[PDB]
Amino acid sequence: KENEFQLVLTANSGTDNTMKITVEGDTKLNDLLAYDSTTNTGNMQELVKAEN
Amino acid sequence: KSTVASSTTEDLKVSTTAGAAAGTYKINVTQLAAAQSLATKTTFATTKEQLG
Amino acid sequence: AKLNVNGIDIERQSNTVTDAPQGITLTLTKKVTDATVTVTKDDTKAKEAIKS
Image (cartoon, rainbow over all chains, first blue to last red; front, side):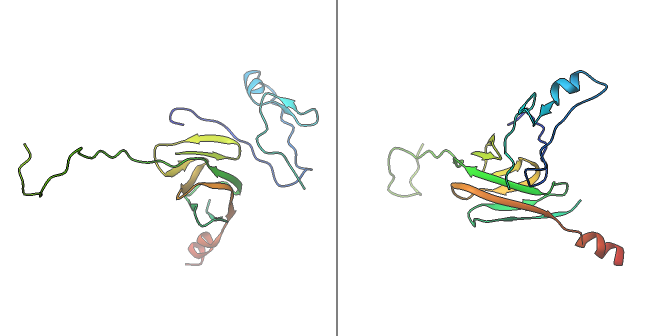
């Protein structure tokens, strides 16, 4: 809504294309962009789940 | 950076400004916006009649 | 107007939603459930410009 913004990362279609994100060199960006899809935990949240 | 968009339903209409990222979006329109309307409590004999 | 795009809640003042995501203009006519909007890249404009 007005005066609020969000960042969305979308992979390709499929369950082989599940992102695992790690930021290297910076600690704040890693605090904001960090997801481990293998363990399904991270700083980002998953809106849409991957399917075949 | 030019793309074209299409919609399954005819109720929703979609157009693409330059810079869009290709993908698929799932859209649920919960509500619709409406504009306030105010009507005089009484009724008048004719327009030419002076009100004030 | 209240809608939901890919699991993100959007609230606007009018029935022309523009910045969800940035670069796609949606015209809402009536309430919808699980509509699909597909955006695919087209290169016709660049090839016409190059040919001319």
